[PDB]
Amino acid sequence: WRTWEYQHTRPDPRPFPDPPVNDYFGRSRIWNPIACKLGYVRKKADEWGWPNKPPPPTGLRYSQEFFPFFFERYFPDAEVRLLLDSVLNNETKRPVFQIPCSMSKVELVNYLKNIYGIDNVVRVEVRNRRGRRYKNEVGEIKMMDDYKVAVVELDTPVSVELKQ
Amino acid sequence: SAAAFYEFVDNNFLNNKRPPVPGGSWTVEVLRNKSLADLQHIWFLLLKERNMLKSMKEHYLRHQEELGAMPAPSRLKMIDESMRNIKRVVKERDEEA
Amino acid sequence: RLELLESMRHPRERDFYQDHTYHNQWLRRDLEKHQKQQLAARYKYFAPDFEISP
Amino acid sequence: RCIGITKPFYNKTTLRAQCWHDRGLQVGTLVFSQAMRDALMDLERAVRRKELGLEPNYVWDRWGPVG
Amino acid sequence: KNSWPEWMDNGADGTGYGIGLHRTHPLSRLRGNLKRSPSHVPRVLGMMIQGVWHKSGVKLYFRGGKPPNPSVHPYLTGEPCPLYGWKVTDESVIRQFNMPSIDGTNFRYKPYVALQKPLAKRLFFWR
Amino acid sequence: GVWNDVQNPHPGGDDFGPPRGPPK
Amino acid sequence: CSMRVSIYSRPGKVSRLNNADATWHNRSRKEKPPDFDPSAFRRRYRDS
Amino acid sequence: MFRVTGLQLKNPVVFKQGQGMFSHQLKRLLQKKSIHRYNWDPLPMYDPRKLVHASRHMDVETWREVPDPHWDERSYLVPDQMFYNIPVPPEYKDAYWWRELQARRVQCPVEWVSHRMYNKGDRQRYDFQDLAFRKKFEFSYEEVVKNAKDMRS
RNA sequence: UUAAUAUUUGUUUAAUGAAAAGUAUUUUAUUAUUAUAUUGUAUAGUAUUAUUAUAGUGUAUAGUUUUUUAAAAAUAUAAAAAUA
């Protein structure tokens, strides 16, 4: 074989493989379990400003005083959205809300009891839902963030009238 | 009771009135002077405001043909900026600690 | 003119994908050359450092 | 045993018979399984038969160690 | 032998209650079957794509239609007991929202800062 | 085989939930 | 994609997502027995 | 290699090899690369942190070891990740010779940094000792200019 | 060009010598109820059922794998005999 004819460059593999970016934005979107190095790097950098600041000791890292957990406990961030159609101009006993996927029935009932004062909560019906997908004018597929649907049941029917 | 849902929903949209855009957002210079308990109080206040704003935005998205674009949309951006500034101040204090 | 175009055709003609598509239409794929050039010609300020300085 | 329990200990620190469930409609009420309810059915049936006066046939009275 | 509990492997309840992927809190002592190892990715991906088939005849995890997202599961709070419906062993995992006390400045504050009418359907609002 | 062939009560493992049998 | 074609909102028609006169035909004609409830079976059996 | 192994495993486990969006997304998600961390081969035959109490005399009164400064000085340091450095008597340092090589070597596959040895500049500016691709010293341009100007040439 | 062509011709009809399901997708919607973590929803279609996880007080108005019309020839139907 004439190997001296070529220069020293690695040819591309055939057939060429696809980029690891998932391009499907449908109902069956899958979460990639493989962990990348950039993910750990970004996590560490947002945690303690890597690599400029020295790392906190293992005790503070694994303790309840570590900045992310401390901020999540003293300044909670939970997006609870009420559906206007479910309670607008109709005396409904099952109002529905939209929450992040990391919450549960107990999380939501504690949220409504402590923040908004809605203590009389009978049962919360949980059901996940894929984020809303749509195309803009140029045809780019942009999907809204995922949200969990909750159907809370109260003892008394509630309604917020709309003054026409 | 019912007041919880009345504050979940908007008031000007409820009375069929044009909601006005507020003045400004919380600045880091102010949040540095504010205290920790005061910071978390205003944080919960901004959280409730953001919940109401997101409920209104989702309602307008559900009815985008019956109702036009959401009036005064910069309020969500102001709330997010205030929350980010709160997080910045708390992170600086935690770094010093 | 959609109603007129449909009325002028013959009823025996049939089209089977009126309500559903064969290939999934949620895979992000590229546009066409002419419309990409239209976009690049209309939106020039999207390029980096388009604003005049100072 | 005659109530219908199979495991004496629900936990290593408490018996299974002394388990009354809180956080519910009936507070302080002892928890009962389907087997417990069926054994209580048998007991109430035998008691009602004995009160009527006919032969009280407790189906578990003929239950020995080998069955 | 595996690290996640054997009830997580095969639910202790008769109907296979408590089987599937359960994400755990970092500070929580309990462990879950959600592992991103190159050797643990095949089973955790099969749990999402196909699911687990039980002996009773019902498919427990991913019954069909829409695949779940294991990364956004709320953190594990306990272990299933046969007596009750659920046994909570970790209470710190469940977040407890709490409101700050009121103050002379607290009831005087407002969400937005004060810088120094009929609704009309419009197609676009700038600010 | 052409002929017919003609069960775990505690799948929680070795020891889970209620204790099984006397200790030691 | 018939739902997104007809029931969804478009620049010519309003959203029919929550509309009984457009959704009532989705229900089955022949009624079907209810599905088995594992949580209900657990709370009913109450294993001991 | 690892990508092909994971692809074959997923194809045998959960891929139906159909035109479904599940397989269409798996064929692209399996190309992602996992975390790589050089794990030194543990030595269960000889525990290095166990030999700390070896070759030491003890006080008969309190029945505990004697902190010999000569032993503390002559102690040889064996490296390990969870146990950063461990002192050990120099008589037993022979059995831990492979850990020394695995620690001196850069904790990275050689073919990732092989672009160093394939050029003259890096071959002269870098070190190749026990497969440790650590950059040597290199004066700054200001430094070399100042040195030459002080040397007057 | 082949081509005024070849093969097709389908909107409740002549309704069928017939009717009890599972599984995997596509698509999703404010269901009710038992009323204690998480997880996957319903109908409608599509593909499949040997190699036991579908058969009983008794079976969906079930009609797209079922298809239009005022001629001879060709061709198919010997279940198209009252022939050989």
Image (cartoon, rainbow, N blue to C red):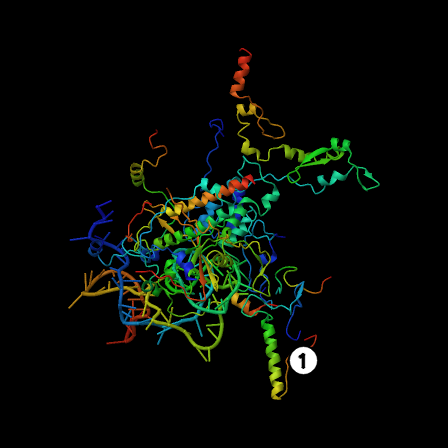
Residue at point 61%, 86% (across, down): D51
Vertical order, D57 against C52 (above or below): below
What percent of the width, then of the height, locates residue H109? 57, 35
Q: Residue furthest bottom?
A: D53
The residue located at (57%, 27%) in the rendering is H135
Q: Position of residue H1 (x, y in %)?
A: 54, 41
**Count the marks: how many?**
1
Say few, some or many: other residues with alpha carbon within 10 Å of mark 1 (under 14 / 14 to 19 / 20 or more). few
In depth, the one of C41 and I22 nearer the eye is C41
**Image quadrant containing the N terminus of chain G:** bottom left
Using residue E91 as the reference point, say whether residue E72 is left or right of it: left
Q: Is residue H72 visible?
A: yes
Give the secondary structure at mark 1.
Answer: loop
* Image coords of residue A21 (percent x, y): 45, 44
Q: Quadrant for residue H130, please give it.
A: top right
| Picture coordinates of residue C27, whole percent (x, y) | 39, 47
Q: Is residue I40 left or right of residue G19?
A: right
Q: Amino acid at mark 1?
A: Arg
Q: Residue furthest front?
A: E104
The residue lying toward the viewer, choosing from H5 and A126, is A126
* Residue with the most extreme top position: H152
- Quarter of image, res E20: bottom right
Query: Which residue was labeled with disc 1?
Result: D62
In the displayed structure, would residue A85 be above or below residue C39?
below
Given residues H143 and H35, the one toward you in this image is H143
**F20 on left or right of I4:** right
Left or right of A45? Residue B62 is left
- The answer, for residue C24, to whether it is visible in the render is no
The image quadrant where one finds the C terminus of chain G is: bottom right
Chain letter for mark 1, please.
D
Task: Name the residue located 40 percent from the left edge and 49 percent from the top edge.
Answer: A143
